[PDB]
Image: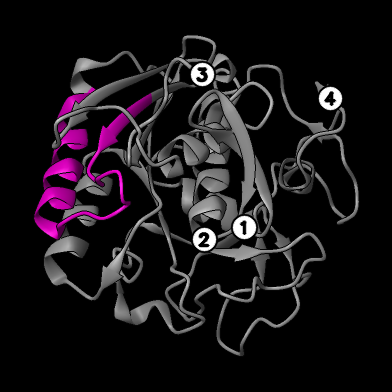
Amino acid sequence: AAQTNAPWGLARISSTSPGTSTYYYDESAGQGSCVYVIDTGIEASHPEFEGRAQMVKTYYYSSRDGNGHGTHCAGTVGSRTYGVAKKTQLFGVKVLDDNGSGQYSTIIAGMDFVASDKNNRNCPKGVVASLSLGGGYSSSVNSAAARLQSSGVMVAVAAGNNNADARNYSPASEPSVCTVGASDRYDRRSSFSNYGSVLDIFGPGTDILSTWIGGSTRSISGTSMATPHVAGLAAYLMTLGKTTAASACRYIADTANKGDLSNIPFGTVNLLAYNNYQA
């Protein structure tokens, strides 16, 4: 399938070259997979989600996304226009308040929630969790991410936006999950992207158009935007049967575009997420 005039990041993930604008992908489109977006919530009523999004958990007075961040990330995972995996089921877990903040104890509870809650959902092609969040190093936060991954969920986490080594941030620094840095439309490391040996992969993160609250759209930047590209890609590849939740990060690295990014510090992988779809 071909989506013309797609957001640059979608075109990038199906291309051997920057500078194109059509996204190519197998029509299975993540059908039968599920992606949890652990964030500020999801505006599930947005027409772009087509009834495939729902809130399943909140730790606050509402499950609504009063911020926009979680809706934007969910749109990159799975919205009809802005999403990688256009037929996945999206489940929102609101661990962040409407200011975008959240206590680590709530974030940990949300991760353990997903590990159990997947057993209450129909996801025959597999389960992914997208975590566009983080703070300073915490062994407990890393352990929660490790448990979620161990339970059979492909965990993708943001590297962070400090232009620093991600070893000092969580859950970015957890080795067993998929830690995602950000790139721009010219294949440069995004100016804010964290780096370091703990990164597994880069995805599009600068000037990413997606859904926003109030039934709207906007373009924003961050490793928060790169992470859902990778989460959606994992769901898509799992639906195709090419990989599993336990092996998808490694498979994405195996099949990535290699050596094409600029300003990658020595010792950080130079790998850009790529669906290897042949139309």
Q: Amino acid at mark 2?
A: Thr
Distance from disc 4 to disc 3, alpha carbons, whole Å, reads: 23 Å
Q: Which residue is mark 3?
A: 46
Residue placed under numbered mark 4 in the picture:
2
Please name the residue that numbered disc 2 is placed on.
Answer: 223
Which is more foreground, mark 2 or mark 3?
3
Residue receiving disc 1 = 205
- How many residues crowd around disc 3 within 10 Å: few (fewer than 14), some, or many (20 or more)? some
- Amino acid type for the residue under numbered disc 3: His
> Is disc 4 surrounded by few (<14), some (14 to 19) or many (20+) residues within 10 Å?
few
Which badge, 4 or 2, comes first in the chain's sequence? Answer: 4
Which circle, 4 or 3, is nearer the viewer?
Answer: 3
Compute the Cα span from label 1 to label 4.
22 Å
| Label 2 Cα neighbours within 10 Å, binned few <14 / some 14-19 / many ≥20 | many
Q: CA distance from mark 4 to mark 2?
A: 26 Å
Q: In the image, is residue 111 above or below residue 36?
A: below
User: Outermost residue, bottom direction?
Assistant: 266
Q: Look at the image and say whether residue 99 sits in the magenta stretch.
A: yes
Please say if the residues under marks 2 and 1 sit with CB atoms less than 8 Å apart: yes
